[PDB]
Each structure stands twice: as C-alpha cells, then as structure tokens.
Image (cartoon, rainbow, N blue to C red; front, side, top):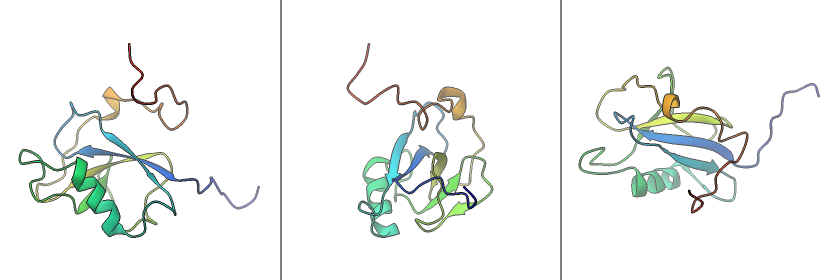
Length: 116
C-alpha cells in the first residue's frame, strides 16, 4: 500500500463542551450518506451540545483537542479524533482524554444501553 488510505466509512469524531471536563462527550460519524453539508452538522451539534449554561446560541466553531487548528468544513476532520465545540468563549485547555482515554475508535467496549 503506497498512498496512505485509512478508509472512508464514516469519520469517527468526538465533540466535547468548551469549558467542561466532567462531560464525557458525544461521538459522531461523518458519513457521505449522513451529513450533506456543514449546516447539517451544526444543527445536530446544537440539538445536543447547546444550553444556557454552555453555548446559548449554539455551535459554530469547532476547534481540535490540542487547540491548534479549527474545523470549517466536513473534509477537514479526521478518522478517530476529538474536537471542542465553541461559540463565543475562548478556547480552554483541559484534559479530556484523562477521563476517556483512546479506546473508543479501536475496541468497541460499549454500545449504549449496556451498563453494570
């Protein structure tokens, strides 16, 4: 394999709340037959990540976990990565992986209702 092609089966991306470490976060699968444009991704993100205490207006700017680059389109994200949903407040450096660890986009050890 001389090209570097991981795949294109829905880009797994985790979105957290800007200024909230307690939050576990919400996963997202960017698939061709799921999200038409960025407007669709913003609508869904606002449906979940949007409250009076955190992001009153909603979601618009989604930065990375490190806080170096900013996502604008759907062809910018990467398979198996994390991003922070921002709006007005400035980016905050917090340890999210500390309470999550990289083990969701490699070994599915949870579906949803399963607990115990």
